[PDB]
Image (spheres, helix red, strand yellow):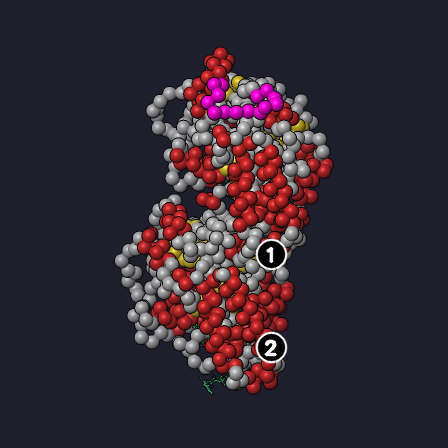
Amino acid sequence: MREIVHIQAGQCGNQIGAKFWEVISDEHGIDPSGNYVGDSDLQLERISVYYNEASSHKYVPRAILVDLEPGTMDSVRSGAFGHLFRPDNFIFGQSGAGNNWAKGHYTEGAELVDSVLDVVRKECENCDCLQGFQLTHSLGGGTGSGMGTLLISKVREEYPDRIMNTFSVVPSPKVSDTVVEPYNATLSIHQLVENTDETYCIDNEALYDICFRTLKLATPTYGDLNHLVSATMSGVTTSLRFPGQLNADLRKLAVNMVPFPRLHFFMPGFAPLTARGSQQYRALTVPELTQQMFDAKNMMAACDPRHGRYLTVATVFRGRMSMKEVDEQMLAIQSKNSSYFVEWIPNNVKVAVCDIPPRGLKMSSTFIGNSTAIQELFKRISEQFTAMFRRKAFLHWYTGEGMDEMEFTEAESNMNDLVSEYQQYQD
Amino acid sequence: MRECISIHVGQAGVQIGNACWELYCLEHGIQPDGQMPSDKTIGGGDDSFNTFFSETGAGKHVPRAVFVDLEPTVIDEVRTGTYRQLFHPEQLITGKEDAANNYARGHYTIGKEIIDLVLDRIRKLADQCTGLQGFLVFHSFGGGTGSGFTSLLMERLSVDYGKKSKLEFSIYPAPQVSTAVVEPYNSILTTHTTLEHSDCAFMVDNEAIYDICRRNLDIERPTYTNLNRLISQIVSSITASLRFDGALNVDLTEFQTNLVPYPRIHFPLATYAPVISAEKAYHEQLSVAEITNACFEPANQMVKCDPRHGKYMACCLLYRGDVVPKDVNAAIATIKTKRSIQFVDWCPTGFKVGINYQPPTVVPGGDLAKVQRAVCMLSNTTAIAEAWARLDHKFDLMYAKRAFVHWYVGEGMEEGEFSEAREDMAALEKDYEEVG
Ligand SMILES: COc1ccc(C[C@@H]2NC(=O)/C=C/C[C@@H]([C@H](C)[C@H]3O[C@@H]3c3ccccc3)OC(=O)[C@H](CC(C)C)OC(=O)[C@H](C)CNC2=O)cc1Cl
Ligand SMILES: Nc1nc2c(ncn2[C@@H]2O[C@H](COP(=O)(O)OP(=O)(O)OP(=O)(O)O)[C@@H](O)[C@H]2O)c(=O)[nH]1
Ligand SMILES: Nc1nc2c(ncn2[C@@H]2O[C@H](COP(=O)(O)OP(=O)(O)O)[C@@H](O)[C@H]2O)c(=O)[nH]1
């Protein structure tokens, strides 16, 4: 039972992670009090990886929540699992998360992260075995990225023989405002690349473009985003939570998935996307499910995979259907869409099936891809930063608290390097 | 007296070990208690089956063998299974970290930090026995454990026991049940470091077994249960010679001599006719000549290859029950009539034969249909070129893009080393091409 320590920080990170944890607990059926009220014994067979044990035999999920605005538990209790997290490790800041990198990444907050690292180190050893670390946040500026990549650097320092993972969200100038973020993102990911190899780029722009246009919305609120993300990035780890064919561990997930030590930006999707409606819907069929699988609109990234090629694909079906027939349409897709995949990497279709269905849904399937497609999103975020770097806007605070211009230029150089790598490996 | 030791490395290896060992215990009249067949009940036996099992004070016939893996996922999963007391508790090792399809992980990261315990246990087991002949290896190409740990372990064995032979039961991997795309990499990385220590290897093909379990065994979704049971049956059909009686292919040295001309080339094909599915009562009957002549068909050849397009080197068989040599020789003569088979131009190539006096034993609660006739061809046909070259081709496709190289590099391999291994096996393909 290789346990996982969950790291989590930031206003958006906590918002997404609360609903994610609620979804996973509900699917596993443990009561919001913290006791097993599930409906079978296939739940607690090895699930200690996410849920530890208390003295009174009640379970206890392990996940750290930190920030720099003092009120987090005041906002963490906004759902249904406030006291559920152990009530001694809600380390809180003092100021807030203005969109200022290095205001958490160099001087203040960095003072707090030493104690944070001490606490997480103390937290880790109690388990029987360690799997690694995985982190949920957004690349959003304002203590959201600083603390994130900072703690990434120190955890990678302390445990080189484990695996990182980021559930970060790329900001976008369609849903949001306070436009200094391109700096924050394109600078933090600049060392996220060297510091981590396991990433999911849930494009907020794509989430809006699919949630407001063709999902019957008028003003997408933050809970609206939280529904879709707490669906997809909660179903992404069912393979970890549930035994099955592709039980691959973090290290093994990587070795099956990441060819090169940098080209590791997975772009996920989820075929039965659903806005918040209590009624489930009419039923869907397996070929329809696996066809909405590659729905370009369905993609949680900013591209249509038809416009590019894949490298290493996974898939996790869920429900009760034809177990052994899924290979038929897997090979059908392979045969009719050879151009979509690449010849450099044969048999890039690792597939598996999980018996359990999700909450409020019978037939569904979480998806993971790895394609050249995210070159489009990176070109977007690179132009949406370079077209404004010429005016040197707002770099006063950054240049005052400990950055410099050469750092900005070298970050742009690194990201042009990544887009070049994607381009050439597409060529 | 004589004896032998079977090693078990990897999840697949230990699953097949459980299946095979349970079948063997069933076959000899032994029971999950092993009360007594007809013998002294303490240090008894005296037939050939003693070479696998040895009686304790209770006459239990403990199988002096071990199971090894780097994660307590499957080892424990069967340690509290049917044969809990058949094997010795604290005689099944459990690793901690899975090799995770990484050959270097089993070669220089975690297996290297535990191999000492495995060596101590196997050496103690050898001290317990008195008549060791060699070793039986159950591993797989694809897995990091069953390749890296396998290679390193057998290297240690060849270092300390430099005389005895050894036989490898590996599993040639298939895309249809593939759980990695680093699988050719691990396969090459281990096999390029086997010939120097390996003596003979019986590799089984997943796609071939899958096609057997479907096209004739009436399955559509075969799990590891179906494939594993079928391969356990075929492995029993191979080793029955060592299990019972003096006949063709009794000893491991005899195995290799009857089979292996040249030390580098020691990959022999294998077949086993009865694949008749299940409780489907009777559509036809059985016949010695029928199964013998149908053996040459590419139906049941353990590994997918085209033998009729390649020159042979030897031919051995084996039969279960319903013994009468005369019609056996008549069947040999009938199939002898040179339809398209060929042989070696510089040595006699007779169809060596050794018969056994026991019909096949089928699992008491499984798919296979009870039969009483059987054949088992251990042909040393050169046509395994095709399969090896296919794997090599799948390998060198992904080397122009330097794919996945860093993952192995990070633990102590070398980038250009892979080119050396690829040239080694290109030369081995040339070696197959030499025979013409
Ligand atoms: C043309 O000039 C413009 C002027 C305004 C606008 C719109 C205007 N803003 C920006 O894009 C400016 C971004 C900078 C950023 C700088 C680069 C980071 O170090 C800052 C910092 C943070 C905390 C403490 C100390 C320093 O500051 C801020 O974080 C503050 C927020 C609060 C905390 C003052 O600023 C806003 O965002 C304001 C208050 C919210 N509103 C807006 O949407 C657009 C343009 Cl283009
Ligand atoms: N016939 C058969 N093949 C199996 C079985 N288990 C695994 N395989 C195949 O063996 C290959 C790899 O072996 P695995 O057991 O998956 O790997 P492993 O030895 O556990 O290696 P690690 O996962 O790296 O520790 C794949 O082609 C699997 O499909 C089994 O019970 N029977
Ligand atoms: N995906 C997602 N993005 C959000 C949410 N709320 C705000 N955002 C945007 O994504 C980024 C959130 O990260 P961050 O800036 O660290 O949030 P902060 O801690 O409130 O400053 C910001 O640029 C926001 O504009 C949310 O609930 N989900």
Look at the picture and state if A278 lies above or below B5. below
Residue A246 visible in the snapshot = no
> Which residue lies at the image location 38% right of the left edge and 39% below the top edge?
B220
Look at the picture and state if A35 lies above or below B273. below
Give whichever of B64, A330 is nearer the camera: A330
Q: Residue A407 has which mark? A: 2
Q: Chain of mark 2?
A: A
Residue B414 visible in the snapshot = yes
Q: CA distance from mark 1 to mark 2?
A: 28 Å
Q: Chain of mark 1?
A: B
Residue A73: x and y in percent read 48, 73
Give whichever of B168, A155 is nearer the camera: B168
> Which residue lies at the image location 50% right of the left edge and 53% below the top edge?
A345
Look at the picture and state if B391 lies above or below B384. below
Instruction: Please identify the residue farthest to the top as the structure is shown.
Output: B326
Name the amino acid, label 1. Answer: His
Circle 2 — which element? Answer: helix
> Which residue lies at the image location 57% right of the left edge and 55% below the top edge?
B402
Same subunit: marks 1 and 2: no
- Magenta region: B336-349
User: Is B344 contained in the magenta span?
Assistant: yes
**Main SS of residues in magenta:** loop
Residue B52: x and y in percent read 60, 28
Name the amino acid, label 2. Answer: Glu
User: Is B382 contained in the magenta span?
Assistant: no
> Which residue lies at the image location 35% right of the left edge and 46% below the top edge?
A322
Quarter of the image where ligand 3 sits = bottom left
Disc 2 Cβ-to-ligand 1 distance below 8 Å? no
Instruction: Please identify the residue farthest to the front as the structure is shown.
Output: B436
The residue where tag 1 is placed is B406
Residue B9: x and y in percent read 59, 40
